[PDB]
Amino acid sequence: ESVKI
Amino acid sequence: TVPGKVTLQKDAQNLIGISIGGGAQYCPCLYIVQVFDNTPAALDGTVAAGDEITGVNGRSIKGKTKVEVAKMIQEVKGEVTIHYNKL
Image (cartoon, rainbow over all chains, first blue to last red; front, side, top):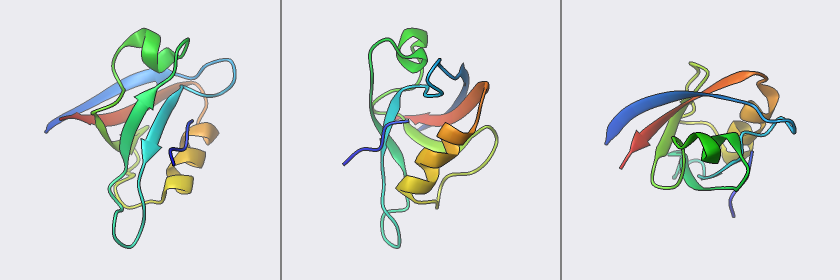
């Protein structure tokens, strides 16, 4: 899981 | 590590374009995973995989949650600064 912003 | 901060401006979709990874109550250390193409973070060539983030626009992230940090950047508009650490 890796939140991209 | 090497403490460094870069002032990257937000894109058209209010997203500098950069992934992260961290937890909470055990892994509060948030870091960067990778970058996306056609992104200000990539085109600029500063923040990307390997560099551990520890700040944003002057604020501190070392302790916040993944969702917290993510929303933090998405909230900020304009010249967004990111204190990354070269490892």
